[PDB]
Length: 246
Ligand SMILES: *[C@@H]1O[C@H](CO)[C@@H](O)[C@H](O)[C@H]1NC(C)=O
Ligand SMILES: CN(C)C(=N)NCCC[C@H](N)C(=O)O
Image (tube, rainbow, N blue to C red; front, side, top):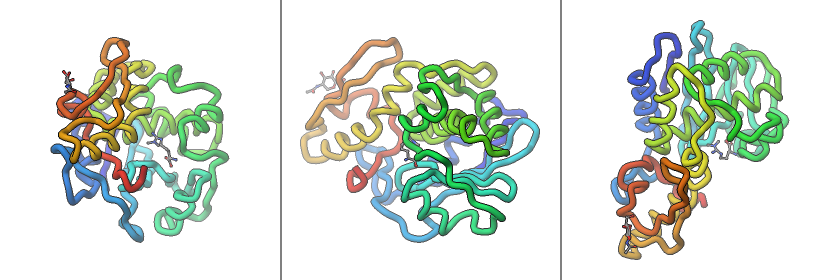
């Protein structure tokens, strides 16, 4: 399990939480010095629990699939909540079993569905540590529209930050003031699966991508990633989705 407390939080404590989250995801192999997430895990060991506390000390526990860093659901007091998708229903067999009641959210966890339910794309949703405090507070008592937006914040400030150093740093900049995600942030989120695949395929293609990945850099400019000597690979990406899950 990993924990994060918004009360007294600063860029340093958030970084320690993201480090903890990365370290809780198992791997047997690194590919170009980046941990390779496992193809599969059986039973309850497939799920990591994150304990998040809002500024007031109230808490949710979030269940994360350790093979892909996908949030499956969360526990708020005695009620569990899960995404409307097969992987999450499976997860509900193993975590939060002692909840008095289980609600299936009226959407899956994919970004496009969540944005529809929330009423806005995440280009327009401010993120940061104050937004995460708000998200935790929202998820404490059920409200499916509010929850969709809260979940978009939660996913980007936990899972996406775990995957990319740049995104972690973006959230650190927003420790005390929310701001919509940078164009590079959205680009990286969208490209994780693509990048994970091309990095694994580069193991037998001399570090060369079979298919180049187009990204936006720290300044809105549309660039092509063609090999493992790229910044994105050497410095930024921190976890690889196993190609067996792509
Ligand atoms: C590989 O990527 C580097 C760094 O982005 C770039 O400068 C170079 O042009 C690329 N080289 C090849 C052979 O793809
Ligand atoms: C990290 N996440 C949540 C995202 N970037 N989107 C990936 C797909 C979501 C998945 N269905 C889920 O269960 O979370």
